[PDB]
Image 1 (cartoon, rainbow, N blue to C red):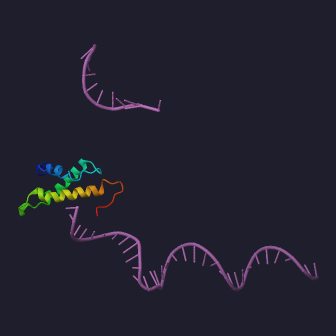
Image 2 (image 1 turned 60 degrees about the vertical axis):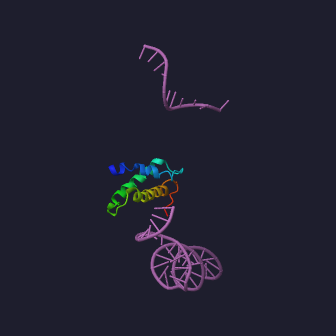
Image 3 (image 1 turned 90 degrees about the vertical axis):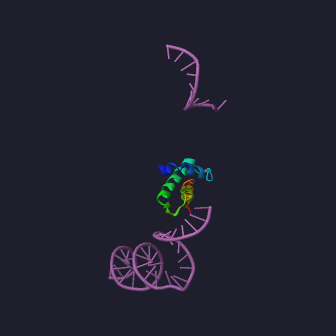
Amino acid sequence: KEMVEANLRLVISIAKKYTNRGLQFLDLIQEGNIGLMKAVDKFEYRRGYKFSTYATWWIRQAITRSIADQARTIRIPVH
DNA sequence: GCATCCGTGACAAACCTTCCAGCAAGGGGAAGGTCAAGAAATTAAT
């Protein structure tokens, strides 16, 4: 909880590059929230990296997944 | 018990799984479509 609450600035700073008129801001924010929640258990911090750098890829994956599944009436898949 | 603030009308990029249609070059099963034999039903001799 404190890990995901200390890094909401990460999702609200990464959600600037995908602010198109397909979805609202809050859906992308809460999809990046579950992407960061997956990155918490996928972190494995013993390599010596920061959480923002590895969490950026997971949150961008969740953002692309939300813009692929949602933001379109005809649901076109992610590929 | 009185002044004052909101509804509401306005002709990215790779990575990996399952699932399904095509072209070989066609055969076979299920299901539905047409030809030559004998049997019903009519008539011209008493």
